[PDB]
Image (cartoon, rainbow, N blue to C red; front, side):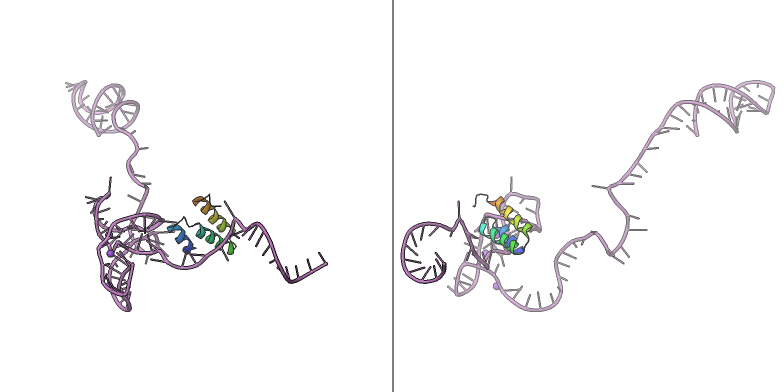
Length: 49
RNA sequence: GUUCGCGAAGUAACCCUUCGUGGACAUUUGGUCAAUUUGAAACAAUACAGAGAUGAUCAGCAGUUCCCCUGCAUAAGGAUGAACCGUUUUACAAAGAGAUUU
Ligand SMILES: [K+]
Ligand SMILES: [K+]
Ligand SMILES: [K+]
């Protein structure tokens, strides 16, 4: 989490990294965290289908 | 305490003196805070190592950041102040062929 948050802090526009971080939380079975990551990504770019 | 008024005692009687009594004057400070270990300062010390773009030695200026420090500062300086360097899979479809199955 520290790694992913560091990268997203330095470059919030990396939508691929946002998705990979959300998937990492999915693999931890922590859907609340995954949902939060997806929501934050939608806050950055809601147009990315 | 003072002062205005009244009772009284002392004095021959006033002034004056004392005991009693009513009124007037003056009227609510300070704390976000307790005095060493357990509600938060840091440097330093010991060790190792010895600065980005390079084959080598270096000037830099920036940008991004939920890192700031020094400075009066919107100046300048702090290794180009530092961190930056990793990890990376699906709007996934169309046409066709040869093998698999009833
Ligand atoms: K050196
Ligand atoms: K330099
Ligand atoms: K500089």
